[PDB]
Image (cartoon, rainbow over all chains, first blue to last red; front, side, top):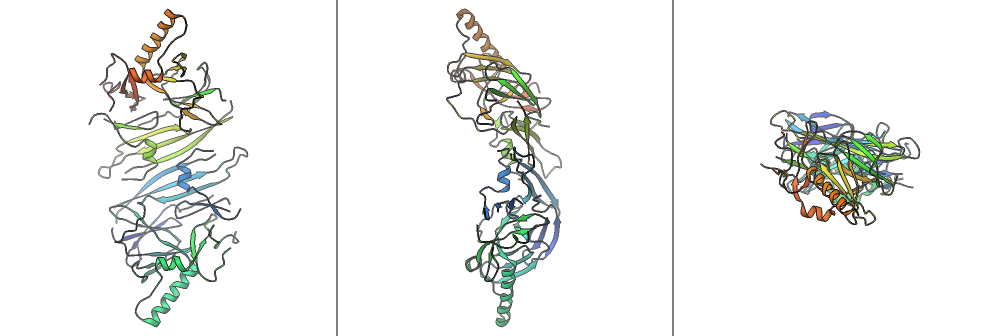
Length: 253
Length: 253
């Protein structure tokens, strides 16, 4: 179980992936990370919240807003579930539901239902020499050796990956990753292969630092079964940066 | 609405009481403050937890244990409800449900369901010249002018009062009170009247300081429809201080 990588995606799919190949061993399909039933743009990656009066980021996440209600009208909720699955691992997720409400009118101004795996905070452990690159609005993943920039594996999961978990010390430990645009991520994987071919010695790829350095901070807004959502991302040269009108990138709020 | 005092009792009764008389204007009957379905002794006054290996107090309350799960097996939950009632006041309470669980066995080691009104923390506001004395395992209340010790009113509610709320700035503000044993509280109200009679000038009563000073810290353990619970309390001379065997007082853990 210490060789598995857990891939949490937007539609509820948790993937038991080979930290080596990146291939699926077993797929667990549950509740979709977000279910905003427009008002607030959630962040599949941690309940963060945004609003569009341009595009701004509030100061409280979804859980926080919940673990701080009633308030003034705010309705909070927080049921927990544990998942039992023999490879037996006890993985637990939390269903956070929030609710806006105006005493003036008589309707639910806003609503959202953001799930999220209980896991230990991510810490820069030198023992982890891997780095993961993720596409916004797409299941593309570029796992590329942290101690170089040497591409370890490319994968395309059904739905966009929202978070990564490694089962350290019997239980999940969230592994920090990078958000890059499909365009740029493909464009990058492309060159990686070209340089790989002309060279014939390894498929290069930027390092989290070079990447986060040379690209350009953007705030991506995606769509999910009629549920919008922002989420930081990097974009390269020649990518438009501001319903189909709101979707896509925007300049960091 | 600024003249009402809200009396939260163990069986779910919220009382709209005259901050002057102490009499009920309107009664709101909802879910009982505790519903431990023996293991952990809850505290109707804030989810605090205790265990009896004598009688000790853990470091985390019920909400905290919930707003910190899943964990390791701990199951948390936190639905909120708002109550609308025209005197219209919007009072909100939170239903906290917790759950213990051993991966070893296959049964729910423990469980509890503690409700609690959303209200602003209590602060020593010099504008509030009242003091409330409460009996453990009884609906006796001795409201006695803070700026003296002069008895303002005596009341006996159906079920034991767990907390007091004052609707300051449109919304509840929890008012700190004192936990004394029925015995002592009756014994006190008694003398108060005797001295009142021989004197014919006012019914005295200790001040939160004299009381909390001359009495003796005890940890009361009560019972509620087959649900035990600890809860600090003061006791005077000649009161036994250690199921009917556990109920009653004990020396401060």
